[PDB]
Image: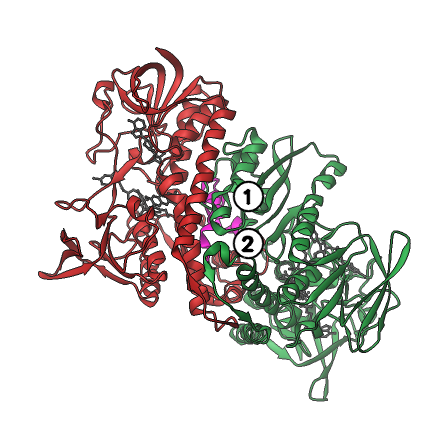
Chain colours: A red, B green
């Protein structure tokens, strides 16, 4: 039985990064993955996803603003090509992971890991073999799986993001359950490629986790794009009759049946917690069936850590990575910085215009008891926005009055996902609106919209 | 007719300074005879970025139609691009007037000439002539095009003004000056099928940037089809009606260049003559730019100078910032000096963009710092690949003492938007170690910055 200082389960964004950090800190490392090196993100998530969003974005432009941009000529778009490009990008990143594992002398174990003890891991190698490994520390980065609508099930026409993302051919129509980022993005792409799209969301607003002002704007954008979004509507059942699928939904005691060629299941993702002997390791779960964890990613078992979607704190790639680093550094006894309140971490939805936020929404900060101060700046008043051809959206900043400290940021606009860094940095290192308003922003850029809010937070904006 | 503050010029610096002044309860009056919003909003910034956007789409299609599964025969009409640039421009200019009324700032439509240290003589556009006194004055007269020594303007030898206000495009053009402005025109024109040749006296293009950036940008422009001649000196320009002949010197040998039009954009001199700066007693510097202290305060106590006229960093956001400092200093409000202007951000908007701040690698080494460099290529960035352009890189320069930043230099798809975090950190003493802990959303270009931070602190992770 080979023995490693550290052993990681799962090669996703969190796993492969936690191994890299471990290796750097001089820790004998081995990573166990049976299928996805780079996990969901690099294989059938983040990576292929954002490549497709880019193709859809172009179709959107060369279709609605072609004339406004002085572009003429009848052009067509082949989704097949978009599909092929997303797979190549995926292949590239995946090949890059192995390079990193190699560069860092990280041992690769190709199979499925199952805890047989708090320090022993039995593996079912992909080539039929079997090998057990011991370890002083273990990092569980097993990820999550798509949660299905209760009672429903997968089939030829009822699928998860996986079967859909790996589909080179597009259906005529589709019904998406869940108005979260994942659901909205597939909607943006598909709709732009000519697919009939209807998105159902139990909650009252699309992207319910975002600030209220953001949900409204985005819903207005999608309705215009031609996508039908039904909020406060419950998906009762899903029936795949082959030639088509029938989904029944209810709202205010009144039911109606929706029908389409396919239906995508995307209401949530449950942490992968069963099937690999967590019980034999003694790792406890939370009431939401997620691996319980502390500020240093430690489970109820001192030497066993849990990172990534599997802990369900913030199911995003950058978070997984970050937690991976924290787990690694803590094991090696090196200097680290707990992520702290995960609500403060940044997040983005990549439909166009983007959605980027961090921290608390206006209403949450209100309920939390802060002396809420708000500054909203519309992009219709931003030079760069008008120059790019998309002056919609806005920048909404939430802060506390006492010292002008940032509580949260909520943005909707062209590629606004790249404007968050400044906000989170200031929030983390006690920089207030006063210090923020003194940062000169290049002209003309979307980032100037952040400068204005800083001013409208400290007092009154200048160009407004 | 007296005011607490009087602003000369209504460009980015003047009109923003007037707003701030007004906000501080100061009676304010601004004098402008032609361009409300100045160069920037009328014939600079605003229309320029609009045209650059159009040219980008032409590029995106031409260069990558196939790669994106976009097939078909499309054609682009510059005239329409032109039309939109004017509309976007007129929109902003109208915005200037709106803010002037909203802040009860008085508009004076004429040219201002100093008579005293507190008196301005105004030649009204209507033909009349009036006088105005003030306790404080802000000079935001901008700059003008500096012509190549011994040459002059003519039918086919123009400045950025004529060129940018031209709805029709030439078949060929020669550009004098490989600065951002010239490079941007080269980008636009080339994408629209114009033969483009850019002549630069200095050995590199974008000579003010970091050498690695100059090298990288020159490569992409050559791939675009733009001919750039560096270490080449423009000797003379002969407008012959049909074709313009530009005599140049490269490698101690004289050769001729020919095109229909020639754009003069090697530099811009601060507007300092013709309006009585001497009557007011304001002193100019060796380079003939109004001298100012860290508060935009000239040798004349109650007289300030902001924008291009002081030549510190000729950019609109710089112009706006100094105006705020001036207005606050005048009212005696809470203010913060801009500090070392070299530490201010700047971006060139060709595609890919160029974005930087602080010192170049060579400058930091020359300054005597304990240079530490971390460079990350976008070929390793998921977002860059998704975008369809993994070219470019992020190059950060820091001092090894505590890991304080000295400069940032990048080239990549819309990198101009990525500077905020860097200038903020350098401004409030946040070192590499602090910056290395800021989480960046995935997948974004900003992640490249994140890797560089780790590189400075020790080892990157995804490279
Ligand atoms: C369509 C889609 C788009 C997305 N877009 C984004 C985006 O733009 N940005 C973002 O930040 N996030 C995005 N996400 C979410 C992101 O993919 C996840 O947050 C991230 O993959 C979680 O990383 P992880 O390492 O925790 O787990 P995963 O990437 O899920 O990897 C876990 C790995 O563990 C392996 N494993 C499981 N059990 C075992 C075992 N017992 N033994 C060995 N190996 C095991 C699995 O095979 C799997 O490959 C997206 C998700 C989807 C579905
Ligand atoms: C083609 C081009 C593109 C550019 N693009 C950018 C860009 O993308 N980003 C950027 O940051 N910068 C850009 N610039 C530079 C930017 O335009 C200048 O830095 C900025 O305009 C300077 O502002 P200012 O207020 O100092 O002066 P200006 O905007 O030049 O305004 C000076 C004003 O003063 C008036 N004036 C002069 N003398 C008198 C007098 N005696 N009495 C009354 N009024 C007077 C003038 O009529 C004029 O309107 C660009 C420049 C050009 C030429
Ligand atoms: C483009 O990349 C993507 C892909 C997915 C999402 C998304 O919709 N998420 C992930 C983040 C989310 C909500 C769901 C989360 O998992 N968190 C916890 C959470 O919401 N709770 C889930 C935990 C849970 C609940 C019940 C049960 Cl039974 C189990 C579990 Cl584990 C916080 N959070 C979020 C918060 C604010 C704004 C935006 C997002 C996303 O959103 C921007 C971007
Ligand atoms: C897309 O927006 C634009 C439009 C113009 C420029 C540009 O070419 N500039 C302005 C900044 C500049 C160099 C010239 C400057 O004015 N500086 C001072 C300066 O050089 N002083 C010149 C003033 C002057 C000129 C002529 C005369 Cl006769 C006197 C004086 Cl005082 C430094 N500097 C700079 C540019 C890039 C990286 C680092 C620094 C630009 O550049 C990014 C972007």
In the current view of this chain or complex, which residue is farthest to the bottom? Answer: B127
Q: Which residues are magenta?
A: A410-438
Residue sitting nearer the eye, A217 or A273: A273
Is residue A368 magenta-colored? Answer: no
* Residue B407 seen in this snapshot: yes
Q: Residue furthest left?
A: A253
Instruction: Bin the neighbour count of mark 1 within 10 Å (Cα to Cα): few under 14, some 14-19, many 20 and up.
Output: many
Report the residue at 74% width, 62% height from top: B197
In this rendered view, identify the residue nearer to me: A84 or B179. A84
Residue A422 among magenta residues:
yes
At numbered mark 1, what does the secondary structure look like: helix, strand or loop? helix
- Residue B104 found in image quarter: bottom right
Q: CA distance from mark 2 to mark 1?
A: 12 Å
Task: Assign a secondary structure to mark 2.
Answer: loop
**Residue ID for mark 1:** B378
**Where residue A225 sits: x, y (%)?**
34, 65
Taking the image as shown, residue B52 lies to the left or right of residue A89, namely right
Q: Determine the chain carrying the residue at label 1.
A: B
A250 or A157: nearer the eye?
A157
């Amino acid at each position: 039985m080979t023995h490693y200082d550290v052993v990681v389960l799962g090669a996703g964004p969190g796993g492969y990064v936690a191994a890299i950090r471990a290796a750097q800190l001089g820790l004998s490392t081995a990573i166990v993955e049976p299928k996805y090196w780079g996990g969901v993100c690099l294989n059938v998530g983040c990576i292929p996803s954002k490549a497709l969003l880019r193709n859809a974005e172009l179709v959107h432009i060369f279709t609605k603003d072609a004339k406004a941009f002085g572009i003429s000529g009848e052009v067509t778009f082949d989704y097949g090509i978009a599909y092929d490009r997303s797979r190549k990008v995926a292949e590239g990143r995946v090949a890059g992971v192995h390079f990193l594992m190699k560069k860092n002398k990280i041992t690769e174990i190709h199979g499925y890991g199952t805890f047989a003890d708090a320090n022993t891991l039995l593996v079912d190698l992909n080539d039929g073999g079997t090998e057990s490994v011991t370890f002083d520390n273990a990092i569980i980065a097993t990820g999550s799986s798509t949660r299905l609508v209760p009672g429903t099930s997968l089939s030829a026409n009822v699928v998860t993001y996986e079967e859909q993302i790996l589909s080179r051919e597009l259906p005529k129509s589709i019904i998406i359950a869940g108005a979260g980022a994942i659901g909205m993005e597939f909607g943006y792409v598909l709709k732009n490629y000519g697919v009939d799209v209807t998105i159902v969301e139990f909650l009252p607003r699309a992207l319910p986790n975002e600030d209220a002002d953001v949900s409204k704007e985005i819903e207005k954008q999608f309705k215009k794009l031609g996508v039908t979004i039904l909020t406060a509507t419950k998906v009762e059942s899903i029936a795949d009759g082959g030639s088509q699928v029938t989904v029944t939904v209810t709202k205010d005691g009144v039911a109606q049946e929706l029908k389409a060629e396919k239906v995508l299941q995307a209401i949530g993702f449950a942490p992968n917690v069963e099937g690999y002997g967590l019980d034999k390791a003694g790792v406890a779960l939370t009431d939401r069936k997620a691996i319980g964890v502390d500020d240093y990613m430690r489970t109820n078992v001192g030497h066993i850590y849990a990172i990534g979607d599997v802990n369900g704190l913030l199911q995003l790639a950058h978070v997984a990575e970050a937690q991976g680093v924290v787990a690694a550094e803590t094991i090696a006894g090196a200097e680290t910085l707990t992520l702290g309140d995960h609500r403060m971490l940044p997040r983005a939805t990549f439909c166009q215009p983007n959605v980027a936020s961090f921290g608390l929404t206006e209403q949450q900060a209100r309920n939390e008891g802060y002396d809420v101060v708000v500054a909203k700046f519309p992009f219709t008043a931003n030079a760069k926005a008008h120059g790019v051809g998309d002056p919609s959206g806005f920048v909404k900043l939430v802060a506390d009055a006492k010292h002008g400290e940032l509580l949260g940021g909520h943005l909707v606009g062209h590629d606004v996902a790249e404007l968050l860094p400044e906000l989170t940095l200031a929030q983390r290192w006690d920089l207030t609106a006063s210090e923020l308003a003194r940062n000169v922003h290049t002209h003309p850029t979307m980032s100037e919209a952040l400068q204005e809010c800083f001013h409208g937070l400290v007092g009154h904006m200048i160009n407004f």
